[PDB]
Image (cartoon, rainbow, N blue to C red; front, side, top):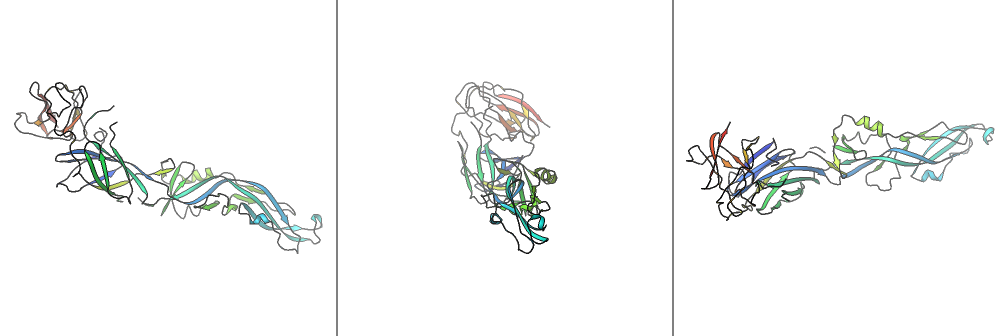
Length: 386
C-alpha cells in the first residue's frame, strides 16, 4: 500500500528473461517491478547516512580560565619565564611593562613580564568530512501481495558503494539480487556539528575560523591551538596582569551559519537525501503459493473500490467456500470474450476466512468487467477508466 499511495511511482519490467533490470531509486519515491511468473516487488530508498566520518577539527566555542600567574623582571635582566609556559593547557603572553623604584627595581625602564592562565574548554563544536564511500543507503524491498496488517515488513537491506552484490531473501518468494551505485552529492565541503545540530559548510572557511582548535584525531581535549582567540590580556602592571576570556560563541556561530544548508541527523550520524541507480535480477524469485486450489466460493467486496494515482484500482475482497486459496481474477470486455488489462498483484490469494485481501489491478481504458471468483456467483463488476 505504501507505494500505491505515493505520487512518485515508476513501473519497470524486464524485456528479457533472467536479464538485469535497471531502476532509479530516490527519497520519497518508489519503484514497482514486474515480470512474467514472478512476484511484483516494491523498492524504496528510505535512509542515506554517513557512519563515523573522519573528524577534521574540533573548535572550542566557550572556555574558562583558572590559575592565572604573573612573573616579571627588571629592566636589564632579560625575559622572565614560567614553567607552565611549557604546559600545553595554558595560554600565555609576553609583554613589556614600566618598572622602577616603586616596584622593586634599581633602574627605571621597561621590564619583561609574562602571564599564563590555564585554559579549560567548556563547549566545543566539530566539523567532519563525509567520504562518498562509507555512506550507507537503506532500501526496503516489499512484496506486492496485498496481504493485510493495520509482521509483514519488506526486507530491509543496507549497502555501501563498496559492498558487493546483494542477495536479499524475501520470505516465501526466494531471493532477489541487486547492486547499486551512488550515481551522482559532493564531499571539498565539511559538516559542522554544534550540539546535535549540523550544517554543511565549505572548507577553508571552517579551517579559517578564529577559534581555538585541536587536530581531529585527539582525545585529550586539552592542548588547544590558538587559545588567544578566546583570550584577552589587559595592559600589564609592574607585577600583575589580568586575563579575561570572551563569552560563549555559540550564538555568534548560529546567527553566522544562517544561509548554509542545514543537515538533519540522529544517533550522532548525519543524514542526507541520496540518489541511487541499481540493477536487479529475479531469476531466484518465484510466486508464493503456486500449486494450490482455485478458490471455489464467494467474495464480498469489503468496501468501495478505489482508484489510485496510477491508472489502477485496489479491490478489497474476502472469502467463503474454501481453502486458503488462489482467487480467480480476470478483467475482460463487456462481452466477456477476451482478456483485457492486467494484475499488479499477482497470484492473489486468501490466507484466512474473513481476511480482506486487497488486490491492485490495471483495467484497460474505457469499459471492462472485473470478474472475481467462480460459478455460484462469479462477481461481475462493471468498470470505466477515464
